[PDB]
Image 1 (cartoon, each protein chain N blue to C red):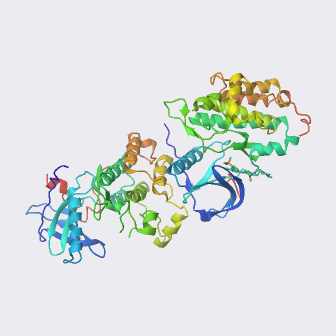
Image 2 (cartoon, rainbow over the protein chains, first blue to last red):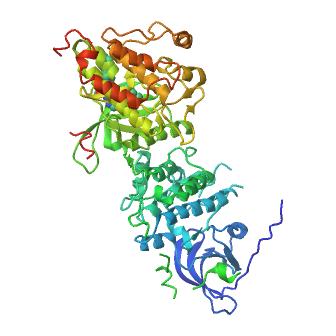
Length: 304
Length: 299
Ligand SMILES: COc1cc(N2CCC(N3CCN(C)CC3)CC2)ccc1Nc1ncc(Cl)c(Nc2ccccc2P(C)(C)=O)n1
């Protein structure tokens, strides 16, 4: 092949600080963290994955393979891996963006978010996944909360808990955001990621409304077998919304492939106003509220 | 062009039940039913279509594309669908045309169909098909069996399982293979699998002769294979007895070999709307002097 001239930074546990916990699991747990590196004035937002136990050689094998893949990931729309840290409990530092996640952004800015932006993010999210899918990497948790805002023009999808097919499947919870075949079998393919990519665009178009809200997670299995999907967002034409219906096809192969979505979504992004209808579309970028919590330096800016 | 703000509603199959099979088909089965929107306290009678097997991705893509057209058309003479059900095998929920195909309607009632309705029914098909010509669409299976009767006064068009859309660039569409009823199709479609609206004027043509004879079998004894031969040779369908030569000439100008020689639907609307201003004059039928909610829920 080619040399994987990928770089692996070793940070010291006294450089990063765990602020609060994000997710948790049997083995492993994910925190919100601030990185203060090598005596600079800058503080960079990050998320840190910690093996819950420090002596488990099968678990320690796993957490390094993931470090391996996250460090091999070099794409503008998948988060970089800032560095690992060899405590007893091995830690991974993925970067975060200073402005926060899309969902919190889209919710806070829906009276000045435009049509060219919404369609421009669908290509960035789809570009990022087809990068991942290009690598036999399944993502298993795509959602607006896991798409971070670098600049209202650039978004990356966080890549913790990726699943390489080292083949037609790999097993492994976010019920609203999952394919039926995931709820009933806890199996994740790339086409189940397409389902997630579906629900992700829905959260975007609705300006951050909650998928299947109030409804219990035990029903979603059933109210999917029976054919209820998310409704049409108001601003969606029937061209946009057919993409979303196709992502939630019960048949997995009937679902759009990721290479297709970007073709389809940039074509619709060259005439943006023809596919999305937003009141006042014609007549602004700024800071967020996740960003207000921190007061604040992008990690892509420091390491340059 | 214009943003297509046509929405499609998604319905879970708990919101409708099927009461009666209206017909088995190669498409599959279509049922008669009541659809009670959850939330709403109306029942709306509906017709529910359900293909044989959702095994192929091609089968799914051709049912969701059939649903894309039906959902975005707002024409009075184009049967519209209410919503879709994304079950394992998807499901289509359309307004129930209570009276059947026109093909069924005019055999049962050959004894009580005056000239006014038959020419009114031809102005209505032509208006729906000129809506479809305006949306760059080719229906590709028009026939009295695919024209449904919501009321004797008002007829609508249906079954876009074979409908195909044109780009702005190409003026004609060409499929391969397929299974299409040979007796309703223009000669170029039989012979080159070419299609275009001018091939659908020919279909419209056969649809009238269907109506004008009160629902006969076109080329009845003739099997499908010979029709290419017989058309090339200049055989066409005979004159309906009810028909004047003014009216039967129009069906002739449809089965014209040259597709642009054939008449545009825009013309067909005017030519038949005049004819319905003096209907006794262009059609001759002995006796002719003598003879829950709905799509009211849409607005
Ligand atoms: C209840 O109203 C109907 C009655 C019948 N009848 C007509 C007489 C027929 N006869 C009666 C006498 N009997 C002894 C032998 C049979 C039985 C079926 C058929 C159809 C509708 N309405 C209806 N609405 C919407 C649709 Cl969308 C649809 N579609 C549809 C219905 C049936 C078959 C195919 C279709 P398609 C072309 C694929 O939509 N169909």
